Image (cartoon, rainbow over all chains, first blue to last red; front, side, top):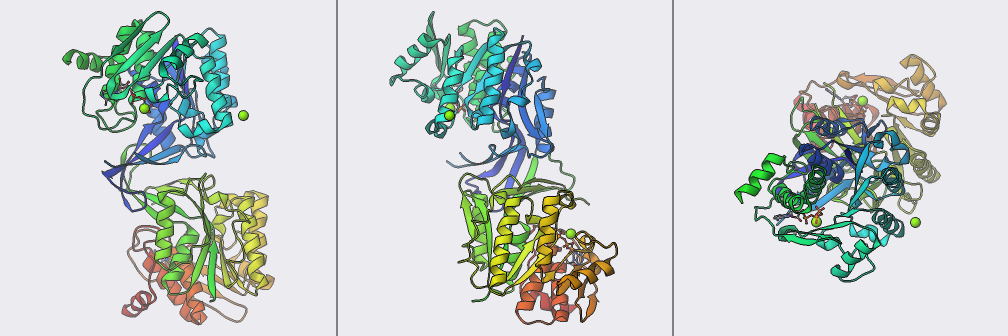
Length: 307
Length: 308
Ligand SMILES: Nc1ncnc2c1ncn2[C@@H]1O[C@H](COP(=O)(O)OP(=O)(O)OP(=O)(O)O)[C@@H](O)[C@H]1O
Ligand SMILES: Nc1ncnc2c1ncn2[C@@H]1O[C@H](COP(=O)(O)OP(=O)(O)OP(=O)(O)O)[C@@H](O)[C@H]1O
Ligand SMILES: [Mg+2]
Ligand SMILES: [Mg+2]
Ligand SMILES: [Mg+2]
C-alpha cells in the first residue's frame, strides 16, 4: 500500500530581508527543496507511510538537492525523471508586512507528460494525490490524467487539493482539467477560499453537498487560523485551530494534506486524522522554508499533548 | 544621431557567496546582477560616452527591471528592450578555477527574441551593429539577427562579430551555418585565441586569419586572455602585452574588451590606440566581481595605462 503524488518539484531561493526587492542586488538563502507535491509527499514519508512521486527535474544541482532530500526521507524517487536539456524549476520569493518570480512552466518540471508516467511504477499504488497547482499546461494534464486513471482503474483512492492559481480558472482547458480530477475524486481537500471554485453552486454548504452527491466520499475543508472541517454522508465535524506564531504559511496546506492521507493510511478514524492534520498544519507555519515545517508523528503528538 | 547597437540575451546573475559552494545544498547567494554578453558589451560602450542601444527581451519581473534600469541609467537607448509577460527573464547561477553554472536562457525570455521584435525604425541611425555569437542558439535568434543585419547593411553600416559561442553549437549544422553566415557579412571579427579556428577551415591561426581577411573581413582583433591581444588587417599587423592585475572574475573581460574597441574606434582612435585601450579595459574588467561591474570610463582606462 503506497501513496503516490505527481507534479512540480523545484527549489526556492528566499530573500534575506523583509522588504528586499527583486530589482536590487542583495543576499538570498537557498536553494531549498520545494513544490507542493514534494512538500506533501515529504510529510507523508516523515509519518512513516510508504510513498513515491512522479516529476521531472533538470540534470543539475537544483534537481539533486530535491532528489537527495526526498530519497533520504524515505520517498521512492524512481518516478523523478532527469532532463539533460532542461533546468530544474525555481522560485525566488520576497516578503513584506508574498512576492515571487517563477520559472516553473518553461522549466524541467513543466516537461512532465504521459510519456514520463511509468504505469509499472503505480502497480501497487492504493492512494494517488493531485495538487491543482500542477495543472498549468496540456502536458501536465495528460500526465495527471494518465496516472489518475491507472490508479482509479486499479481500485485506488484519489485525493485532490485544488491549490490552484485563480487565473487558470479563466482558461477553459485548465478549468476542464480541474473538473476531470474532481469527477474521479474520493477525497476533496479545498481550503475555504477554494470551496466554490469547482462547483455550480454559490453557497459553500450547497457546493459541499453537491460534491458528495456527485461522487466524492469526503470533503476536508481547511480554514487557516480557524481550523478545519470534515464532511461525509455519514458525519460532519469541526476542529478549532491551535494558536501558534505564524512565520510562513506556504506549506501549511501541503503538510496538513500529507498528514491527513498518511494518518488515514495508518488506520486513524476521521476525528483523529483531522486532529493530527490540524496540528501538522499549525506546526508547519511556525517555520520559514517550504519543506522545513514538516513534522514527524512524535512532534505532532507532543504538540497536541502540550495543548 | 549615429548609434552603436547590439542584440541578444539579457539576464541576471546570482553568485555563490563562497568558493566551493555547491548548487545542491542551502547557502548564501548574492544578486541579482545585470548580465548577458550583449548587455555587458553595450554597457561598456555607453560608459565610454558613445550613444548606443540594444534589442533584447526580458520578462515582466524585477529581474527584467534591474537590467532595464541599469542600462537606461548608464545612458543606453533601451526602447528595443521588449517585455514579455508570459516569459521569465533569463538567469544564471554561478559558483567558484571553473565558474560552474546553471543557465536558464534558451527557455526563458531570451530565446523569445523574434525577427519581428526587431524593427528598423529603431535601427535607422545605426551605423555599427555588433553581434555576439552566444546569442545564436535557435533559428528564431538567427532570424532576428539576420533581419537586423540586413537593415544595417542597407543603410551602409558596419558589422562587428564576436564568436563567443559554446563549441557545442558547431555540431548542429543549422547553427553552424548561421555563424558562418554572419561571418561572411562581418567587417570586424573579434575571436578569442581559442575561438580563432572555430569558424575557419584552416588549422593554424596565421592561415585562419589570412582567410577571414581574404573573404572580406577588414579587421580581426584577437583576444589572448592574460597575454594581451593582436590586431590584423590586410595592411598591418601588431600585438600588445597584457597588463598584470589581480584577476577576480573573467566573465565580462571579452565583452568589455569588445565594447571598448568599438567605442574607441567610434571616437576616432587609430588601431594602435584602440587596441591598447581595449586591452586595458579588459584588464580592468577582471579586477572586480560581477559580470557587468567591471566596466570603465574612458579616463579610468587612460590613468590605468598611464600609471603603469
Ligand atoms: N495560522 C495558523 N494557525 C493554526 N493553524 C493553521 C494556520 N494556518 C494554517 N493552519 C492549519 O493548517 C491547515 C492548512 O491550511 P491553510 O488553510 O492555509 O491551507 P490551504 O488553504 O490549502 O493553503 P495553501 O494555499 O498553502 O495550499 C489549516 O486548515 C489549519 O488546520
Ligand atoms: N587575467 C587577465 N589579465 C590581464 N588582462 C586580461 C585578463 N583576462 C582578460 N584580459 C584582457 O581582456 C581581453 C578580454 O579577454 P578574454 O580573452 O578572457 O576574452 P574572451 O576570450 O573573448 O572571453 P569571453 O568568452 O568572455 O568573451 C584580453 O584579450 C585581455 O586583453
Ligand atoms: Mg480545452
Ligand atoms: Mg491557502
Ligand atoms: Mg573566452
